[PDB]
Length: 142
Length: 158
Image 1 (spheres, rainbow over the protein chains, first blue to last red):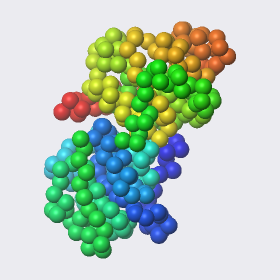
Image 2: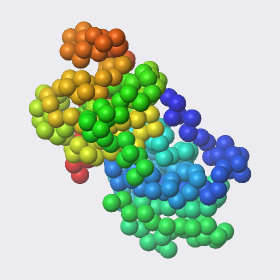
Image 3: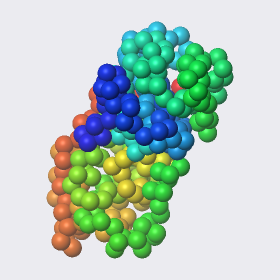
């Protein structure tokens, strides 16, 4: 239950933001079932910065998505708890919206990362983060 | 990549054993698909000691087992990598024998722990560990419902 110290609310993370070590790294995902690509990439993202925050889609927000699985088999608290058990993760935050844009606006990462092959230029959040001079990049699973 | 520092062979861990923080806690399992019960259990096992070592059954070892189905969804190195990524885990070793008895012989853990209500007196490794002044005990482990498990396996396959 000690890794649970990482589960935090958007408001609490927002208050704490100014005291986080730079550079702050952010990523988001469903993380329904953890596999080796997830953790390999979660570890590399941590290596890019001093602090790693993971945003986790709420059950619903997960339901507003056509590409990935429709109903995650694990409830948002369980998906978040697994992430928190990870050595490389510092903070795990849930968000309800369909996209992580307002969460990212609130968190204000210096570095935004995505796992997989994803055009970062096609992402709203890339523009958001680069908009204030941050970096956005994709890190491959394998 | 940093977390892979924890994946080690029996011989190297055995040679390193004397300098590990005591008490050394050992547990073993297949750990096919991690769930919250697993990580809750591993944290509790870690809290019993100063150092946690996880024995991971080899794919061949699983074949050899009558537990659940006859095979695993993830190969041994992926199952070991997942565990090594956990904050509470210090060392992950894979064994190929039917049971972890020999590995436990080589590792010499001070505390053997098992999740669930399991008669520890019926395990050879319990007597072995108690034989050199160590401890063996069961601590509650939360299993996921069979349905969720079957849904999980399917998902993995997909």
